[PDB]
Amino acid sequence: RGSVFQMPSTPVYPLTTTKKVAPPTALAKRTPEQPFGWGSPVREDRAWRVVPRNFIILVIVYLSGWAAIKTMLPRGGSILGQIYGGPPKGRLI
Amino acid sequence: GSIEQFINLRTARMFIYGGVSAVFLYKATPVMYRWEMLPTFLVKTEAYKAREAMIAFDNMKGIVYGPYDKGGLEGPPTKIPETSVGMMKVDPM
Image (tube, rainbow over all chains, first blue to last red; front, side, top):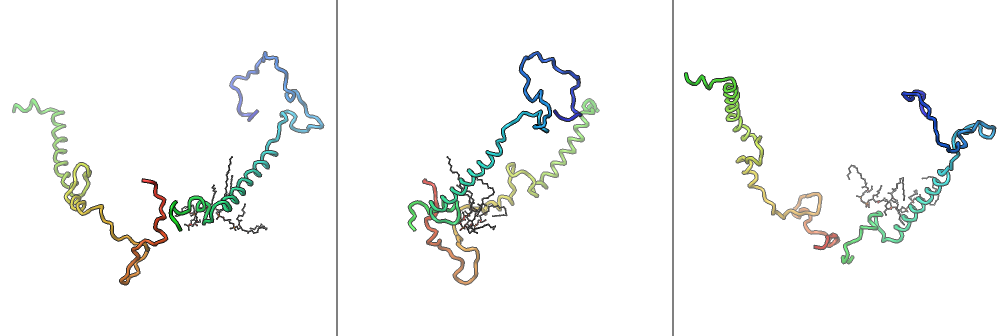
């Protein structure tokens, strides 16, 4: 809700005429099963699945590309060398 | 007598100030010209022309392929190495 210092200049509470059903957490209470957090809606924890998945993909792409470059391109001093480091076309060595 | 009609504050302020300026420029302009303070596009000094007349852009000598001149009678290498001939990736004319 924020700091106790920020406040409305005029202290008004809306007489909501909408008939929407109350969210479950809005009427919730502390319970033995839920000592904390009973006022916040439960959510999915995407980080637990997305962080290890994304990390694996990036490592696979990083290593696979590195292996590929260093095995599917002619030998050279650096990666940029193996890509743009050959002699001009038509220059026989 | 008969000049008083002209003599006036505005006619005097533009006569002293303006005349003072007439001598400030007449006496300072030659100094600025001598010391190369005038803009080049407006005028070129004789010294400027003398130096510029000595500049050309058609000298194709002195090409060397080594960082040092180690004396002697042979001098620095002047022949392009064979391994470097035809190693440039010049775009098609």
